[PDB]
Image (cartoon, coloured by chain):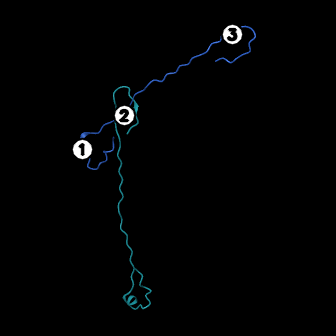
Chain colours: A cyan, B blue
Amino acid sequence: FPTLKEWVGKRTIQQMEAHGYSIANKTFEGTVGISRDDFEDDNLGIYAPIF
Amino acid sequence: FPTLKEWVGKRTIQQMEAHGYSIANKTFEGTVGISRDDFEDDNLGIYAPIF
């Protein structure tokens, strides 16, 4: 609200202001490729924790 | 009251002083106007916190 000012004549109508702002989303990706043979020919379990 | 001076002859009649000071009252005002259309058509709530 405007700061109060001395009342000399008749009330003066004044104006306020409104603001706006927006942020747009984005998409992200990441992928890897492990061959079927190497994944299946694995007794050690070294490749197991990829998830 | 006058400081006490040494008495030698007669008594000298001094005088004092009174003081005054006044502060006058002032009138302040502030006014904001929004159209009825703009107030009722607001479906967002931006103009709600004016009071």
Query: Label 1 sits on what residue type?
Result: Glu
Give the number of the disc on residue B12.
Answer: 3
Q: Indicate the position of residue A39 as horizontal and vertical percent values.
A: 39, 88
For the residues labelled 1 and 2, the Cα–Cα distance comes to 23 Å
Q: Of A23 and B2, which appears nearest the observer?
A: B2
User: Which mark is in front, 2 or 3?
Assistant: 3
Q: Are marks 2 and 3 on the same chain?
A: yes
**Which residue, given by chain and number where applicable, does mark 1 sit on?**
B40
Subunit of label 3: B
For the residues labelled 2 and 3, the Cα–Cα distance comes to 60 Å
Report whether B23 appears left or right of B9: left
Query: Reading the chain from its start, which is encountered first: label 1 or label 3?
Result: 3
Report whether A49 appears left or right of B21: left
Subunit of label 1: B
- Location of residue B24 with respect to A12 vertically, above or below: above
Q: Of A35 and A13, which appears nearest the observer?
A: A13
**Which residue, given by chain and number where applicable, does mark 2 sit on?**
B30
Q: Residue at x 38, y 90 (%)?
A: A40
Query: Label 3 sits on what residue type?
Result: Thr
